[PDB]
Image (cartoon, coloured by chain):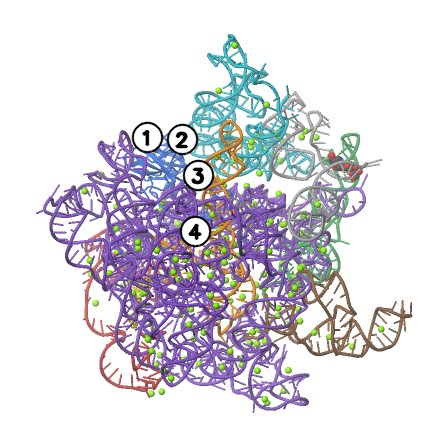
Chain colours: A yellow, B blue, C brown, D purple, E orange, F red, G green, I cyan
Amino acid sequence: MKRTWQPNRRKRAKTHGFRARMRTPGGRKVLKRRRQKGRWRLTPAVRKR
Amino acid sequence: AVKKFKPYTPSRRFMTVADFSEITKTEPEKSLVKPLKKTGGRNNQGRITVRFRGGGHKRLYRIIDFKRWDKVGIPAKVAAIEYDPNRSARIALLHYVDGEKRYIIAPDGLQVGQQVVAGPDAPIQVGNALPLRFIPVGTVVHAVELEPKKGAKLARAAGTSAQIQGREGDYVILRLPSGELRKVHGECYATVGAVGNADHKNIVLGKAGRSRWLGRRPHVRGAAMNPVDHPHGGGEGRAPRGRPPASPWGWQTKGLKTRKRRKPSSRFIIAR
RNA sequence: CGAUGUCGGCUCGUCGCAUCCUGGGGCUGAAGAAGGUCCCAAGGGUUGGGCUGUUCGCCCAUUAAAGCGGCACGCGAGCUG
RNA sequence: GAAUGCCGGCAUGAGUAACGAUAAAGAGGGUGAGAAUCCCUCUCGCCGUAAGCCCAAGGGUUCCUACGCAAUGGUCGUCAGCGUAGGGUUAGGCGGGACCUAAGGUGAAGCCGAAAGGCGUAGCCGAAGGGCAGCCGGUUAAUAUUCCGGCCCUUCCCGCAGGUGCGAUGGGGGGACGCUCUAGGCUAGGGGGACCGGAGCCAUGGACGAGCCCGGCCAGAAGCGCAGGGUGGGAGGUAGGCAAAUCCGCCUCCCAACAAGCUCUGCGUGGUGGGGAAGCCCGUACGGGUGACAACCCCCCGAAGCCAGGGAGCCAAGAAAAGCCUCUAAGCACAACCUGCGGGAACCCGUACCGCAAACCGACACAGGUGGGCGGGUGCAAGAGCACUCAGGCGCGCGGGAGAACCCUCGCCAAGGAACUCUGCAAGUUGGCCCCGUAACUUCGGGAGAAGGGGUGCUCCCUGGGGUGAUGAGCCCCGGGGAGCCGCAGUGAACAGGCUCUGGCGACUGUUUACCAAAAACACAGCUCUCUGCGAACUCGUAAGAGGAGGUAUAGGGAGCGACGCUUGCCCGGUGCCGGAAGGUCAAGGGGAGGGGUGCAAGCCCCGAACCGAAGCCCCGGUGAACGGCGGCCGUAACUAUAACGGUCCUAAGGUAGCGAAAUUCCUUGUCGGGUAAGUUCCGACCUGCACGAAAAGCGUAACGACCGGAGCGCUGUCUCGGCGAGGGACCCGGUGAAAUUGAACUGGCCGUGAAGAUGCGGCCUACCCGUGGCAGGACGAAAAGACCCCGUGGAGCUUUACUGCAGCC
RNA sequence: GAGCUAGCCCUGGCCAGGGUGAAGCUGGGGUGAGACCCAGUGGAGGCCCGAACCGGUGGGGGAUGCAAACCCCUCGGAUGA
RNA sequence: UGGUUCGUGGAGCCAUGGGGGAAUCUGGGCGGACCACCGCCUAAGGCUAAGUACUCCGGGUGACCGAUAGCGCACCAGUAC
RNA sequence: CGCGGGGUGGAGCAGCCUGGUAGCUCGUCGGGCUCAUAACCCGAAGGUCGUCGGUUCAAAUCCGGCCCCCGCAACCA
RNA sequence: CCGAGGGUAGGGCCCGUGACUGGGGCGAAGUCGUAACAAGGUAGCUGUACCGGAAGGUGCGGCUGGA
RNA sequence: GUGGGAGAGGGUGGUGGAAUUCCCGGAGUAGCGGUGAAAUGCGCAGAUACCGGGAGGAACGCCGAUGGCGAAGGCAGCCACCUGGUCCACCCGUGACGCUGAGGCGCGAAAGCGUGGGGAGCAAACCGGAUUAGAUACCCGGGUAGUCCACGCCCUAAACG
Ligand SMILES: NC[C@@H]1O[C@H](O[C@H]2[C@@H](O)[C@H](O[C@@H]3[C@@H](O)[C@H](N)C[C@H](N)[C@H]3O[C@H]3O[C@H](CO)[C@@H](O)[C@H](O)[C@H]3N)O[C@@H]2CO)[C@H](N)[C@@H](O)[C@@H]1O
Ligand SMILES: [Mg+2]
Ligand SMILES: [Mg+2]
Ligand SMILES: [Mg+2]
Ligand SMILES: [Mg+2]
Ligand SMILES: [Mg+2]
Ligand SMILES: [Mg+2]
Ligand SMILES: [Mg+2]
Ligand SMILES: [Mg+2]
Ligand SMILES: [Mg+2]
Ligand SMILES: [Mg+2]
Ligand SMILES: [Mg+2]
Ligand SMILES: [Mg+2]
Ligand SMILES: [Mg+2]
Ligand SMILES: [Mg+2]
Ligand SMILES: [Mg+2]
Ligand SMILES: [Mg+2]
Ligand SMILES: [Mg+2]
Ligand SMILES: [Mg+2]
Ligand SMILES: [Mg+2]
Ligand SMILES: [Mg+2]
Ligand SMILES: [Mg+2]
Ligand SMILES: [Mg+2]
Ligand SMILES: [Mg+2]
Ligand SMILES: [Mg+2]
Ligand SMILES: [Mg+2]
Ligand SMILES: [Mg+2]
Ligand SMILES: [Mg+2]
Ligand SMILES: [Mg+2]
Ligand SMILES: [Mg+2]
Ligand SMILES: [Mg+2]
Ligand SMILES: [Mg+2]
Ligand SMILES: [Mg+2]
Ligand SMILES: [Mg+2]
Ligand SMILES: [Mg+2]
Ligand SMILES: [Mg+2]
Ligand SMILES: [Mg+2]
Ligand SMILES: [Mg+2]
Ligand SMILES: [Mg+2]
Ligand SMILES: [Mg+2]
Ligand SMILES: [Mg+2]
Ligand SMILES: [Mg+2]
Ligand SMILES: [Mg+2]
Ligand SMILES: [Mg+2]
Ligand SMILES: [Mg+2]
Ligand SMILES: [Mg+2]
Ligand SMILES: [Mg+2]
Ligand SMILES: [Mg+2]
Ligand SMILES: [Mg+2]
Ligand SMILES: [Mg+2]
Ligand SMILES: [Mg+2]
Ligand SMILES: [Mg+2]
Ligand SMILES: [Mg+2]
Ligand SMILES: [Mg+2]
Ligand SMILES: [Mg+2]
Ligand SMILES: [Mg+2]
Ligand SMILES: [Mg+2]
Ligand SMILES: [Mg+2]
Ligand SMILES: [Mg+2]
Ligand SMILES: [Mg+2]
Ligand SMILES: [Mg+2]
Ligand SMILES: [Mg+2]
Ligand SMILES: [Mg+2]
Ligand SMILES: [Mg+2]
Ligand SMILES: [Mg+2]
Ligand SMILES: [Mg+2]
Ligand SMILES: [Mg+2]
Ligand SMILES: [Mg+2]
Ligand SMILES: [Mg+2]
Ligand SMILES: [Mg+2]
Ligand SMILES: [Mg+2]
Ligand SMILES: [Mg+2]
Ligand SMILES: [Mg+2]
Ligand SMILES: [Mg+2]
Ligand SMILES: [Mg+2]
Ligand SMILES: [Mg+2]
Ligand SMILES: [Mg+2]
Ligand SMILES: [Mg+2]
Ligand SMILES: [Mg+2]
Ligand SMILES: [Mg+2]
Ligand SMILES: [Mg+2]
Ligand SMILES: [Mg+2]
Ligand SMILES: [Mg+2]
Ligand SMILES: [Mg+2]
Ligand SMILES: [Mg+2]
Ligand SMILES: [Mg+2]
Ligand SMILES: [Mg+2]
Ligand SMILES: [Mg+2]
Ligand SMILES: [Mg+2]
Ligand SMILES: [Mg+2]
Ligand SMILES: [Mg+2]
Ligand SMILES: [Mg+2]
Ligand SMILES: [Mg+2]
Ligand SMILES: [Mg+2]
Ligand SMILES: [Mg+2]
Ligand SMILES: [Mg+2]
Ligand SMILES: [Mg+2]
Ligand SMILES: [Mg+2]
Ligand SMILES: [Mg+2]
Ligand SMILES: [Mg+2]
Ligand SMILES: [Mg+2]
Ligand SMILES: [Mg+2]
Ligand SMILES: [Mg+2]
Ligand SMILES: [Mg+2]
Ligand SMILES: [Mg+2]
Ligand SMILES: [Mg+2]
Ligand SMILES: [Mg+2]
Ligand SMILES: [Mg+2]
Ligand SMILES: [Mg+2]
Ligand SMILES: [Mg+2]
Ligand SMILES: [Mg+2]
Ligand SMILES: [Mg+2]
Ligand SMILES: [Mg+2]
Ligand SMILES: [Mg+2]
Ligand SMILES: [Mg+2]
Ligand SMILES: [Mg+2]
Ligand SMILES: [Mg+2]
Ligand SMILES: [Mg+2]
Ligand SMILES: [Mg+2]
Ligand SMILES: [Mg+2]
Ligand SMILES: [Mg+2]
Ligand SMILES: [Mg+2]
Ligand SMILES: [Mg+2]
Ligand SMILES: [Mg+2]
Ligand SMILES: [Mg+2]
Ligand SMILES: [Mg+2]
Ligand SMILES: [Mg+2]
Ligand SMILES: [Mg+2]
Ligand SMILES: [Mg+2]
Ligand SMILES: [Mg+2]
Ligand SMILES: [Mg+2]
Ligand SMILES: [Mg+2]
Ligand SMILES: [Mg+2]
Ligand SMILES: [Mg+2]
Ligand SMILES: [Mg+2]
Ligand SMILES: [Mg+2]
Ligand SMILES: [Mg+2]
Ligand SMILES: [Mg+2]
Ligand SMILES: [Mg+2]
Ligand SMILES: [Mg+2]
Ligand SMILES: [Mg+2]
Ligand SMILES: [Mg+2]
Ligand SMILES: [Mg+2]
Ligand SMILES: [Mg+2]
Ligand SMILES: [Mg+2]
Ligand SMILES: [Mg+2]
Ligand SMILES: [Mg+2]
Ligand SMILES: [Mg+2]
Ligand SMILES: [Mg+2]
Ligand SMILES: [Mg+2]
Ligand SMILES: [Mg+2]
Ligand SMILES: [Mg+2]
Ligand SMILES: [Mg+2]
Ligand SMILES: [Mg+2]
Ligand SMILES: [Mg+2]
Ligand SMILES: [Mg+2]
Ligand SMILES: [Mg+2]
Ligand SMILES: [Mg+2]
Ligand SMILES: [Mg+2]
Ligand SMILES: [Mg+2]
Ligand SMILES: [Mg+2]
Ligand SMILES: [Mg+2]
Ligand SMILES: [Mg+2]
Ligand SMILES: [Mg+2]
Ligand SMILES: [Mg+2]
Ligand SMILES: [Mg+2]
Ligand SMILES: [Mg+2]
Ligand SMILES: [Mg+2]
Ligand SMILES: [Mg+2]
Ligand SMILES: [Mg+2]
Ligand SMILES: [Mg+2]
Ligand SMILES: [Mg+2]
């Protein structure tokens, strides 16, 4: 059947990107938490040009 | 007149379509004056706030003239009468000698080629606009302003009118389509005649689809729902309500008057 | 009750006898034929359909007879639903 | 030592299940330490509106090559999409960006919000939408509309040359738009040819033949040619197009009425460029040569594509913005702009490979899911359907044998057909086209593919229409008529309704419980009630704001009913809603009679009665397509029986019509009638309706239904009642190799006994040790710390005239 | 968190081929003028058959599956809500 | 209405959203309703070290662990997944 | 089986809960009006209060046991 | 070839019959009431319409077969 | 044909006043309605009676008749348009063109039906109050369809002289 993962580079970027997270206090805290944690990747790596 | 069909299909046996014979050879509209992009959307910034809206034909807005006092004294020739997707009525395309082209909402009896004009001057004829004062008591009228210089707001639906009843210092009394008795300021413009396309009420949609074409989504009964959804939801195999009938939001829907009492508008109203 | 699947049906049977038939027999208000009633006896047999989910039962047409009951109202790691 | 404990390890089942589609394999040779699995050749099979080719998304080294086999590969592996290394992705013209706007996002101005933040005209952002200049060939082991060859275009910038008032983010025009049906000419694509090109071929009985086989194009500026789209021309007047315009709009005289002319595309032609089969020979993993000076032509079919902003009809009435033309404003007119010509300048990113899939989404080389374009040929009425087949690509990464049960999938069956069963569940029968021929009933459309029939192949003769061609040939579609041949059978294989009668429910197409319910449920036109005067009612938000609606009573919200026909009775006492400037009560507040506390006092401080005080409730009316409700007991007619009739008690009033043992009927298989050999079902009746009933509508209703019930015909393996055959497993051999479960076990029957159902205790009987294929009675077999039940002063969702609050409104 | 799913907004795409033959139009018939009736034409429709496509009706398989919804046969809709 | 031990309590004090609304030392607040007396303070402007808190960082020590412990990580771990 | 409600002149209902008095309508009887019946008018009769018990000074009434009648309930399996 | 008829399939008309139901006619002395004939005690009749155990009532207009 | 005449003949548009009902303002009280008699009902929450203003619907007093017109059904305030029949005079024109009429077609009171509007008065049904043995009747108080307009059906009658 159709499963739940339907990859889209634009969606992933607009949805979970560094700039989206930065836009709101909710998201800014996510970066803070991930930084303090020592996460190698703050936001998902969306590729291609 | 109303177009009628033979039952060559079920739902074609009741279905019924407007007569478009008053639609003069001018079916597609007029750029310049209108159209605008019209912005379909069944809801506010976010959430739906009027249920069951959506779908249905794309539209172009015809930006019509609801304040006729710009062109006081300037007459215009009625050039055409065309279909307007965004109202029950039809619209008149008129050419002002000025050059300017406006649409007026098209009254019953309006003929193409006719002369029409607005102002204190203005022969009392079908199509003309006047401040309510100079209009003879008892004449039927439409596109009436509520307060002066604020635009036509009463009687624009197909086949509607108001009748002038009497006067009272600065106000003339109106009898509105609903039957209400209203004091409306003398200085309010209103155009003589009834609205026309009066056979609009006689049309039978005929099937579900037609409803959808006009963007009317299926309306579901409270009875059909559940207690979480509606006061009428549940219980077992059908149910008669079990309380005084209500809206989904709990207010009673048979009888409960809802106009706020202390409206300052009150001292200008005399009926139902 | 940290689970013993619960009606009926189908399939496969098997056991009790307080025996429906067939075999043996005493009494009969048993002429004979055919009955009635009890005793002995399970070796084997104990039909096909209409109705109802039905068990059961009432019919239809037969039969030597159309037996009763137990086996977790026998049998769903066999089936059905 | 136990916690269905936690982590780790190793056991058991067990060499057991499986090895991922029943499209399928065989052989010779090569390579290698090793080959069913790699390479090659021949043979065979499968796909072919794909299982073939091209885009996009996603993926990200998977592409090419060399060297490799520990692991990954469900077996093998010399192979690989795997390991190591190196190589590989070339653009002003394709896509995206130095262009435009859509929804939506952001957001100066501004409005709002405890903070965070929310709203928001302008503008900015935002694309499979608009705008927008490259086609054909050749080369690489791997890239090409990118490199190369040919031919052709676009922007800029600088010059010359000739024109003109040039000139804005501003005005106007244009861009610019729906659905269905389409005309004319073309192209793509295809079919055919005695004509042209071509290596070769006579087999196996005959054919050296107008023979078989293969192939007979592509792109292409200017200029034409042919199709077709676009568009009137002047002169006045001028108050509108938010300044100004010569532009645009409007008005008026003229000249056109036409595509005449201007244009603008499509197609054809075109300077030139380029390709070019079978077959044969080679050595490649694959390609190279020759065939070739290849020829490169004529008919015919023909789009859904092109001309395209084409036409007609219809109603539900069909984006914006820039480029583009034109108008003028500031200004500048040694400026600038338009045209022709040279010359120069032309950036950033993507470009490999996979792409219906072993490379994307499903933990996997997973039988699933994934948008767009091309998708040949014959035959079947047509077609994207079906059978075979081009090109092209595969045989699905375990095999070998065997020929048990049993299972899956498939084929046939005597006689009989529903006797099968909850149910004809399943399966059969039927099946396409053409032509005859069709009942009730009906809303006059239907029911209708009703039912039921006949024709269907091949050959010869005669004949009638078109289309392309000149009015003719041919080629191409449609037809008619007459004789004749063969078979069991002529849509000879593949695709292709079983039918009828009759109830119930719902009008109908539709919608739904993604993953057990597709329905009689939801929806639906339509009906009715009701609220709403516009800063509408109502809905979301604390707000601002927004939806309603750029709508205005023929409108919008809410409720119920649910096409249509006929209809929808009586009850307003209770509840609700509506209407009542009276009265009763009623909070803050006003008011202070009166009292109290301290003060030597002036004072300060408290209570505090009358009375004035809203909504609300009470109270008075209305209101049932508002919540709802719509009786009991006696007696009576000249056979009985029954009761039109009377009496009486009660109510706010005591269910009318219509319907009725029902999707309602307990007693119930009510009682009659019908179908049957027989009928707890069904149908028609009666009415004693436990417990119908008139918009939670009543009674009907043609048409409709993968709805539920009853019957019949047709037909059949459902059945009597089974039998045979096929293939995939099952079994044996080789390779690989799991699982839940598992206190340990050396794990028999009976009769007892035991917590009341014992392999394990007692007694007796039976019983050599170990497997394998099978059947499932048991180990209260596995699986889930029972869902039912109860318990817990456990939790949740829902309700209301439970309590208490809150929003909300008054 | 709406890359699944439900609704809506913006902008694109898709639906082979067959039937049936509504209004309208043209002619004729009729009439004072009509209504109306015949042909021919026309191509309407939550019309019909049926692929693609979107579904999921019945049955069988599958049940440590190919698959945490699949496969086979059968079936609904397919110019429209 | 909050705050204080203070939950309306005899409920002050301190802060305050609403209404009314002064005075400048013979002025004003407080000492738990209120009043008299005796006392204490001087609101409606602001700044002010030190003692006090914590431990990403460096050091020191441990009747602290010794790779299932000790930080999740003694090992390129906030990684693989 | 369980629950709660009901038996009163000839008929249908009151009277009980706050025990002492049994009343209402119809009917029946006698008389009148009428030619005659009814209607109407004037007079009158008529109740072991389902039975068994006792509580009281006294039971239709209050309490128990039966008897008929009416109505509801009988669920989760 | 046609062809008596036979078989199959579906229609049209008529006759008979059927649980039950509708009204009708008729049958000396059963029930309820008083509709009409006298101004029949509400003039009657009437087409239509609604309602009622029944005659019938009432609405609308008409009629003289009434003043 | 010419020249006239009378008429509620028909269709559409428009318009007048009387009265009823309702609302509003005034002034005003204790009863008003109604019948055979009553009661329900309306009325101190300010009725009835009276004045003033407003809205709305319907029917047209007097003229008016035993009268007029039409083929009937039927038609009645006034005005205008559109229009049918009709009678008189003059004897000018045509010249037998005439009468009737199965079917057909059109019209056709009232009630009723459909869709929409309208709804003051009246009023089937329905509800109350009396009356009666009982009244689903007659009398009284309320009251819905309907009565009114448009358009479309319906086709009856003591449609009668
Ligand atoms: N009689 C003719 C038609 O039928 C009905 O009439 C029938 C009945 O109504 C009528 O019944 C009458 C009754 O009215 C009257 N008041 C009392 C009388 N005893 C009855 O009589 C009837 O029944 C008896 C026995 O039962 C028979 O013997 C007698 O013949 C018969 N007429 O008897 C008739 C039967 O013959 C209509 N009423 C009458 O008007 C109609 O036109
Ligand atoms: Mg625009
Ligand atoms: Mg947002
Ligand atoms: Mg609904
Ligand atoms: Mg529900
Ligand atoms: Mg609720
Ligand atoms: Mg129910
Ligand atoms: Mg109820
Ligand atoms: Mg409810
Ligand atoms: Mg248990
Ligand atoms: Mg256990
Ligand atoms: Mg014995
Ligand atoms: Mg004997
Ligand atoms: Mg036996
Ligand atoms: Mg049968
Ligand atoms: Mg059965
Ligand atoms: Mg049993
Ligand atoms: Mg037995
Ligand atoms: Mg038992
Ligand atoms: Mg059992
Ligand atoms: Mg069983
Ligand atoms: Mg078992
Ligand atoms: Mg079941
Ligand atoms: Mg473990
Ligand atoms: Mg085993
Ligand atoms: Mg095995
Ligand atoms: Mg195996
Ligand atoms: Mg495989
Ligand atoms: Mg070798
Ligand atoms: Mg094939
Ligand atoms: Mg790699
Ligand atoms: Mg490779
Ligand atoms: Mg190699
Ligand atoms: Mg391997
Ligand atoms: Mg594998
Ligand atoms: Mg090797
Ligand atoms: Mg590699
Ligand atoms: Mg640049
Ligand atoms: Mg941009
Ligand atoms: Mg932009
Ligand atoms: Mg914002
Ligand atoms: Mg584009
Ligand atoms: Mg481009
Ligand atoms: Mg490549
Ligand atoms: Mg190329
Ligand atoms: Mg090039
Ligand atoms: Mg522009
Ligand atoms: Mg070509
Ligand atoms: Mg040749
Ligand atoms: Mg030979
Ligand atoms: Mg060819
Ligand atoms: Mg060419
Ligand atoms: Mg200007
Ligand atoms: Mg070549
Ligand atoms: Mg066009
Ligand atoms: Mg712009
Ligand atoms: Mg210029
Ligand atoms: Mg590339
Ligand atoms: Mg590529
Ligand atoms: Mg594809
Ligand atoms: Mg594989
Ligand atoms: Mg796959
Ligand atoms: Mg995969
Ligand atoms: Mg697909
Ligand atoms: Mg094709
Ligand atoms: Mg093909
Ligand atoms: Mg073909
Ligand atoms: Mg075909
Ligand atoms: Mg195919
Ligand atoms: Mg091969
Ligand atoms: Mg057989
Ligand atoms: Mg046979
Ligand atoms: Mg048979
Ligand atoms: Mg049977
Ligand atoms: Mg049976
Ligand atoms: Mg059946
Ligand atoms: Mg079947
Ligand atoms: Mg039929
Ligand atoms: Mg034949
Ligand atoms: Mg029925
Ligand atoms: Mg349905
Ligand atoms: Mg489901
Ligand atoms: Mg679905
Ligand atoms: Mg279905
Ligand atoms: Mg289902
Ligand atoms: Mg309806
Ligand atoms: Mg909101
Ligand atoms: Mg708004
Ligand atoms: Mg709006
Ligand atoms: Mg509405
Ligand atoms: Mg319903
Ligand atoms: Mg109706
Ligand atoms: Mg009702
Ligand atoms: Mg009530
Ligand atoms: Mg009331
Ligand atoms: Mg009430
Ligand atoms: Mg009130
Ligand atoms: Mg007070
Ligand atoms: Mg009050
Ligand atoms: Mg009734
Ligand atoms: Mg019955
Ligand atoms: Mg029978
Ligand atoms: Mg029977
Ligand atoms: Mg029945
Ligand atoms: Mg019901
Ligand atoms: Mg009832
Ligand atoms: Mg109801
Ligand atoms: Mg219904
Ligand atoms: Mg029914
Ligand atoms: Mg039906
Ligand atoms: Mg359907
Ligand atoms: Mg269905
Ligand atoms: Mg079988
Ligand atoms: Mg086999
Ligand atoms: Mg093996
Ligand atoms: Mg042993
Ligand atoms: Mg035992
Ligand atoms: Mg033992
Ligand atoms: Mg032992
Ligand atoms: Mg074994
Ligand atoms: Mg087994
Ligand atoms: Mg178990
Ligand atoms: Mg438990
Ligand atoms: Mg439960
Ligand atoms: Mg408790
Ligand atoms: Mg979505
Ligand atoms: Mg088609
Ligand atoms: Mg014609
Ligand atoms: Mg036609
Ligand atoms: Mg069509
Ligand atoms: Mg369709
Ligand atoms: Mg279809
Ligand atoms: Mg396609
Ligand atoms: Mg299925
Ligand atoms: Mg299908
Ligand atoms: Mg279809
Ligand atoms: Mg506090
Ligand atoms: Mg307290
Ligand atoms: Mg304050
Ligand atoms: Mg203070
Ligand atoms: Mg103080
Ligand atoms: Mg102090
Ligand atoms: Mg103190
Ligand atoms: Mg102090
Ligand atoms: Mg200070
Ligand atoms: Mg400080
Ligand atoms: Mg240690
Ligand atoms: Mg550790
Ligand atoms: Mg260690
Ligand atoms: Mg750890
Ligand atoms: Mg007497
Ligand atoms: Mg339960
Ligand atoms: Mg329960
Ligand atoms: Mg014959
Ligand atoms: Mg008969
Ligand atoms: Mg009489
Ligand atoms: Mg009378
Ligand atoms: Mg009478
Ligand atoms: Mg009458
Ligand atoms: Mg009446
Ligand atoms: Mg006249
Ligand atoms: Mg003469
Ligand atoms: Mg005649
Ligand atoms: Mg009539
Ligand atoms: Mg009438
Ligand atoms: Mg009616
Ligand atoms: Mg009507
Ligand atoms: Mg309607
Ligand atoms: Mg009245
Ligand atoms: Mg009356
Ligand atoms: Mg009234
Ligand atoms: Mg007649």
Name the front one of labels 2 and 1. 1
Query: What distance separates the C-alpha of mark 2 from that of mark 3?
Result: 30 Å
Above/below status of D328 relative to D202: above
The residue lying at 29 percent from left, 73 percent from top is A38
- The residue pinned by badge 1 equals B122
Secondary structure of the residue carrying numbered label 1:
loop
- The residue pinned by badge 4 equals B52
Do the CB atoms of the residues marked 4 and 3 lie less than 8 Å apart? no
- The residue pinned by badge 2 equals B138
Count neighbours of disc 1 (C-alpha within 10 A) and say few if under 14, some if 14 to 19, many if 20 or more: some
Type of amino acid at the residue the image marks with label 2:
Gly
Using the rendered view, name the quadrant where residue D394 is placed. bottom left
Count neighbours of disc 4 (C-alpha within 10 A) and say few if under 14, some if 14 to 19, many if 20 or more: some
Do the CB atoms of the residues marked 1 and 4 lie less than 8 Å apart? no
Name the front one of labels 2 and 4. 4
Who comes first in sequence, dot 1 or dot 4? 4
Query: What distance separates the C-alpha of mark 1 from that of mark 3?
Result: 32 Å
Name the front one of labels 1 and 3. 3
